[PDB]
Image (cartoon, rainbow, N blue to C red; front, side, top):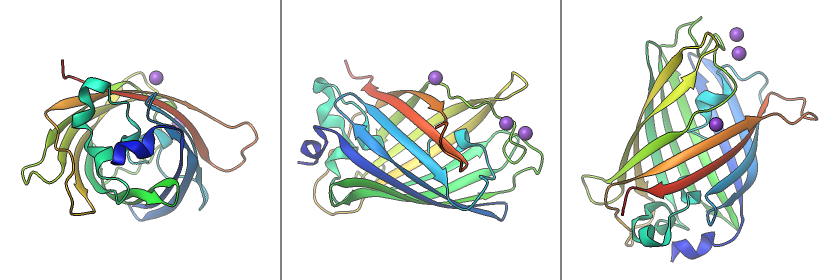
Length: 225
Ligand SMILES: [K+]
Ligand SMILES: [K+]
Ligand SMILES: [K+]
C-alpha cells in the first residue's frame, strides 16, 4: 500500500509561498528522505531575496511520511497510508508574545518525487520581536509531536510545542496545532495515540550565495509498547 513507496530513498521537492506581515517570499527545497531510517536531508533556498523570518521558524512547515515507524507501530502510520494521492496538512503556529503562522500544504507524489507544496500567512508580528527582528539562534531543539485520530475519523489531529532558542539565552515557544486529511477517498490507517520523537541539525553550504538552510532530521515514532 502506501508504505511500500517508502522502503528506499525517495527524492523530495518543497515549495513554499509566504506572506508575513505583508513581507512576501518564496522558498524552494530539494533533497531526499529515507523513512527506513527516519532521515531527511534537504537544502532550502529563498528564491525571492532575503528571508524575512528566521529559517528555524519555518522548519516544521517545510513531510512526516518520512518518519520511521517501528515494525510494531506500522498500523499507526497515517502519513504513508495516504500516499500516493497524499494529504492536506494545515497548521496554526502561535509564537508566544508574538504573531502566528497559518499554513496549508499538500503532500503527495508527483512522479517518483514526494512534493510538499505550501502556502503560509503570518500576521500580527512585532516589527522588532524575535521573528521579524531575526533574534533566533541558528539551531533546533528535539521535540515530541503528539498524534491522535481526528474527530471525523478521516485523518489526524496533531499537537506539539516547538522551543526556539533565542540569542539572549531565553527560549521562545511556538505552539503548533495541526490537522491532516487525506486527499483520496479510500481507506487510510487511523492511529492510536502516539508521538514522533524529532531531532534536527542545521548548517550552511559554503558555496551557496543565496539565503538558505541545510537541514538534516531524524524522526522516530514511539509511545506504543
Ligand atoms: K538580528
Ligand atoms: K540572528
Ligand atoms: K539538535
